[PDB]
Amino acid sequence: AYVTQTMKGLDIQKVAGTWYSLAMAASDISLLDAQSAPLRVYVEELKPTPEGDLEILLQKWENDECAQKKIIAEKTKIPAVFKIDALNENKVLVLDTDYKKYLLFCMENSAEPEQSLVCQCLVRTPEVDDEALEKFDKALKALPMHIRLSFNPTQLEEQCHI
Image (cartoon, rainbow, N blue to C red; front, side, top):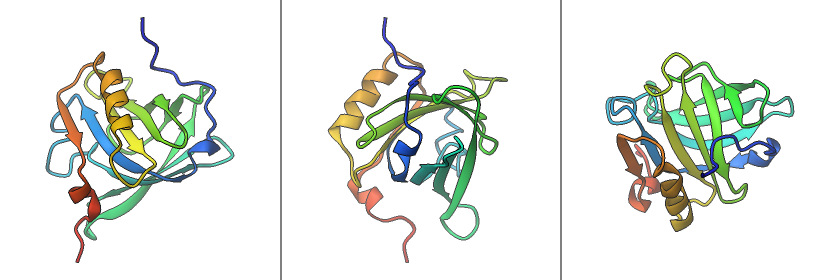
């Protein structure tokens, strides 16, 4: 039996700094495929507050060509569980992480978890890392899937630049 659901005993402030995307695996194609999918978010920064909330700074096309947003994830009870109110997922579970390496989280809705099941991994290094790839693949090999995404140095280099 594997163990990868509730991180627990995780330092909130430890996730304070700059982050990056490495891969994304959503159950719903329309959720993360094209047409500015809700899940389709180009995370860039991540830093929570001393209270317990988590500042999820993501960059998604809103109107001003690649706009940067921020979600104030509220606390519930367990550090490996947060509550948000923006995208198609209020629940936020923390799979795993290495503090100064990468982070693995999942999003779902109590109303339709399986329908809102989505997991992604964020790397601290400004570039892909065979570590975040294998692990994220080994941890997702046990859960469902539908659409995967693997950013590349070419695509990560720039985005909608002038």
